[PDB]
Amino acid sequence: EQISISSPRKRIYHNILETIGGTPLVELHGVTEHPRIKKGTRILVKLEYFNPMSSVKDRVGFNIVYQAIKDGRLKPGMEIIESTSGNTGIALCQAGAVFGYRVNIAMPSTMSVERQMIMKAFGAELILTEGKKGMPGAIEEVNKMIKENPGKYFVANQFGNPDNTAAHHYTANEIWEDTDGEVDIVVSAVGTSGTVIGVAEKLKEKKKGIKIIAVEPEESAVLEGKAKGPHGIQGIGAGFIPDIYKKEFVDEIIPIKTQDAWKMARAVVKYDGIMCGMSSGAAILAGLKEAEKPENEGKTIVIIVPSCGERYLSTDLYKIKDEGTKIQILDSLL
Amino acid sequence: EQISISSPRKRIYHNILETIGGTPLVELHGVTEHPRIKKGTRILVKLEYFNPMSSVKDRVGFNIVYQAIKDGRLKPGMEIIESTSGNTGIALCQAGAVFGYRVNIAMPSTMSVERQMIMKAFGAELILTEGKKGMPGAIEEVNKMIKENPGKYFVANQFGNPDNTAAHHYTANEIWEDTDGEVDIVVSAVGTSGTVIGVAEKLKEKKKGIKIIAVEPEESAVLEGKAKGPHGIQGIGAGFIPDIYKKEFVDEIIPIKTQDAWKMARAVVKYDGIMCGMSSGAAILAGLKEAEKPENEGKTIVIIVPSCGERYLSTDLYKIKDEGTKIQILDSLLNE
Ligand SMILES: CC[C@H](C)[C@H](N)C(=O)O
């Protein structure tokens, strides 16, 4: 029961973008204490909120913008633009601030107000579109802006841009190195699908046998061929199959109910002291469901945790008060 | 010009407490581009929001609870208690969750309701006290519970606990290591003073000549012997000299005005893309003022950044919008 904190990094970073990646892989113990999850089975969570702006999208905003600059797709005098009301817009504002590019984020005026403030703090221009029109309204205005100003804008295009997927070759390498090649199964909740496919690509290059599991809301199970539907797992369930998705790289898809995802996240912060977001709740429950299968005994399971619960305080994540013991909570989840 | 992201940690952490510390030391560039700051001077920020709950206090809550467990001051059956409405509360809740101890946090019922929800998520019991009584009301209640329940509670006592100061021997080692011994000046905005003293204690062992600079609100300059007063630099300016403060380890104290601290933090996010909190605004401004002094040319200046601006969205930090170009903003901040 000796407990050592982290050693010095022994690096001086040249700017904040160099602190992106190399996120920690942490053992779960509290939510894994269940008679069906066997002793040898290892359940690890990769905590992407250790990134400078606390989400997986940091890797994406950075790679998209940096590659575009190296490529000549983004050049001085041009501006970045994207329709997004989430973590991607924040990641793009961070990259844009460092590189010295104006960043334009379009989103329905109904959204965030807090993420709006984050994006403005970074110096972003916000393009608040008509609330009723939702994200299609934001996309529409960006298209209108590109058309009216040819040559001026670089569109991030998070669902169609392969520099998204490619960023997660680093995510995969970290998993490989950190588990010393022992990883057996990776679980990733799917938004753009950059994580699941980019991780899958790279890991399957390392070891064909690795099982890759995508997670999506049961209420909007589009990867499994269902229709787009309302759901409350923020960050995932985009309602279409992203163009960067590659089904060949995904071995199984697990649908998780919105309410279960939230309830899992509540249990994780309570019993492991890890304050994960909503989509993490879904990924972790899927991973726990894998860990209880007899054919998975002794395997190493890695679960992506894309964001931190702090970004969800204005939501319903921590409203519901679950009852029963820990074993009771976990039984109702499984 | 090559930007390289971080390499794999090559470690599997047994639990989240093992990810505390080893925070990154990052160069500032955008906010250092002012004629009075010399090219050779290195201005670095140590980003304590890389801790798992996003503040320097993760170290403190961890070490307080860990040492108490190792010493026998915290034993199965007892509960943790503290009156705090800041980051220390969250740090204690995380430590408590992992070690398997109950955490009781007392604060005024009207303060940091975001932070309230964070704490309840970790399973903490909140002791919400009368709003208009503020922090002395929460302390009074904790004193009451302590008195009526002798032996039940372990009080963190962040302002008086040497385990707070001792945690920053790690902070100091990271600074020493990361700069390969080249650190010349450390700038730290003072709340409990755990950071500035614990860092000074350890670094002054390494090398004669490391200047240690404390930072406090201009409106409440108690370290400098002025009277307590109202200020808006959250996390610092406690209004008294903490029991763990040791003036002999501090070379200079810099007062910073609230509105300047905020304006600095706004400039840092906008021009360096680093979303630092209010007290970081204060420390960075003090550090840039140091970087201006001709005797400091070519020196390595390390500035502690205790928290991320995202924890401040409800405050006026980003509500006030600065007119003017980068150079006008920086010039207005170094004004005098
Ligand atoms: C001086 C105030 C301190 C730093 C703060 N209230 C905290 O405990 O987090």
Image: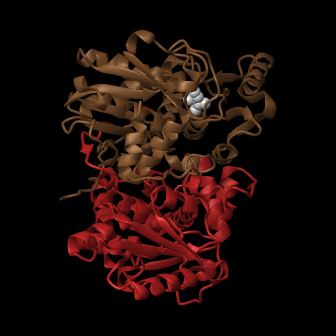
Chain colours: A red, B brown
Q: In the rendered image of this protein, does residue B80 appear above or below residue B311?
A: above
Q: Residue at x 56, y 58 (%)?
A: A117
Give the image quarter of residue B88.
top right
- Ligand 1 is in which quadrant of the figure? top right
Q: In the rendered image of this protein, does residue B193 appear above or below residue A166?
A: above
Q: Residue at x 50, y 25 (%)?
A: B216
Camera-side residue of A10 and B270:
B270
Residue A307 in the image, given as x and y percentages of width and height: 50, 59
Report the number of numbered marks. Answer: 0
- In the picture, the quarter occupied by the C terminus of chain B is top left
Report the residue that reaches farthest toward the top.
B248
- In the picture, the quarter occupied by the N terminus of chain B is bottom left
Q: Residue at x 49, y 37 (%)?
A: B261
Residue A31 in the image, given as x and y percentages of width and height: 57, 53
Camera-side residue of A270 and A87:
A87
Residue A184 visible: no
Residue A139 visible: yes
Give the image quarter of residue A111.
bottom right
Residue A125 in the image, given as x and y percentages of width and height: 48, 67
Q: In the rendered image of this protein, does residue B137 appear above or below residue A3?
A: above
B38 on left or right of A178:
left
